[PDB]
Length: 145
Ligand SMILES: CN1CCCN(c2ccccc2CO)CC1
Image 1 (cartoon, rainbow, N blue to C red):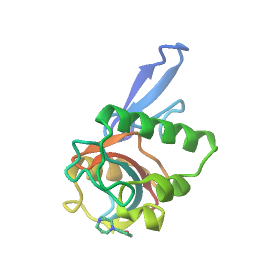
Image 2 (image 1 turned 90 degrees about the horizontal axis):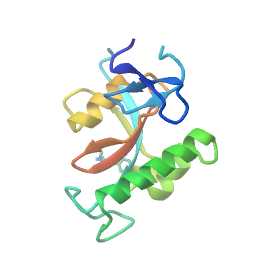
Image 3 (image 1 turned 180 degrees about the horizontal axis):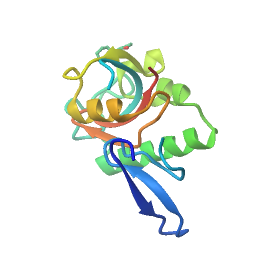
Image 4 (image 1 turned 45 degrees about the vertical axis):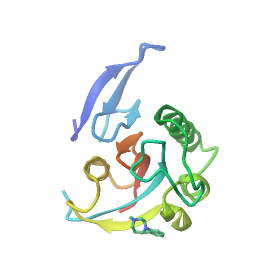
């Protein structure tokens, strides 16, 4: 299996699925390095973020648990097609990159926070992460290039 993937069993259904311990992605189908990648992200900050402040809120007070719940809800709506990633990032990302639909541009290893970097480079082009934790908060990462 490609880097980071492992087999798992659904508790509610008993069906096998695949989970990536670098990106926290999970999916039913069997999963299918460049100098640089390009990613977008949706950041949800929490009270223990390195800077608990954003363009949405002068004082971010939500707990890490609450931020994870919000991230999980956004992932559900993206996966169902009810909402697009770019739309949720523009409206609800606590990163200033919200104004660019979450786009961060292209980057190399050694530039981003390590959990973010590792998830970004383990995604295939077009793939989306699960919740990724950094000192900034909790991220949904979309690899675009
Ligand atoms: C990564 N950080 C430093 C760079 C500035 N950021 C940004 C802000 C507003 C629009 C676009 C971007 C990057 O695409 C993101 C924060």
